[PDB]
Length: 240
Ligand SMILES: [Cl-]
Image 1 (cartoon, protein in one colour):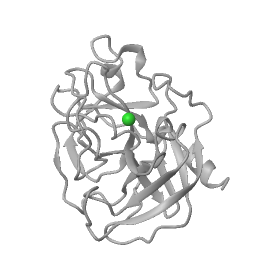
Image 2 (cartoon, rainbow, N blue to C red):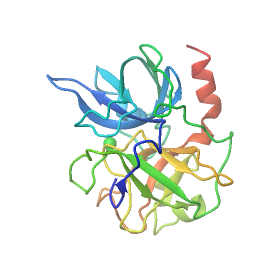
Image 3 (cartoon, rainbow, N blue to C red):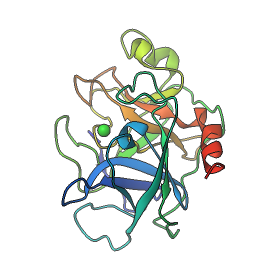
C-alpha cells in the first residue's frame, strides 16, 4: 500500500498474509481474505505458480510476535477456470484456497462479509485497501498491515480512455487513482473493504496497477469484483 498508514491491529480481522517458501525461508507474497474457517479468497495470479503456501491469520507485524497469529498450510488451490496465467487484463483473477485445517475464530480472526450477488457501488464510494504490499513503487513490503482510503471509480469512468480503457472489465472494480494512494505489489489477492449502506464488505480482490507505477493519477488500483463471483464461490465451497 502506497500513501496509506498503519492500520489498527484489530480493524480488519479477515485479512490474511499469504506466504510461500521455495527456499529456506517463508516470504509474504500476497494478501487474502478469510471467508470460511477453512477457505481463503485471494487472486489467481498469486497462486498459479509456487508450490508451497501457508496463510497467516491474526497477523499484523510480519517481523514480530503480535501474539495473536495462527499459521496454517494451504491444502488445495482452486483457481478460477477462466483465469489465464500472466493475464490480469482478461480478468477472472480470483482463486480459493482450502486450508489444511480450520483456523480458530476470535476477535482477530473473523470471516470477511461478502457483498450480495451483483452488488456494485456508486461512483466515489468509500473503501479501504489493506495489505503488506510495497509502500513505494519498486519499494519494499510493509512490516505492519497498512490501510489506504481509495474511493471507488465506477466502470463508466474507469473504462474511459484517460483511465484504464478496455483493459478494465465490468467484472472488475476500480478504486483510488489520485496519484498518491494505491495498492502495490504484494497487496494482490487482499481485500478492498467498501462501505455498503454504512458498513464495510470485501468488494474487491486486489489484482493490478499501472506499469508506470503503483500510485498513478487516473490509474486507479484494479480489483476483481467479488460480487461477480458469489455463485462461483458458493460452487467451489460446495465442491470441496
Ligand atoms: Cl503482486
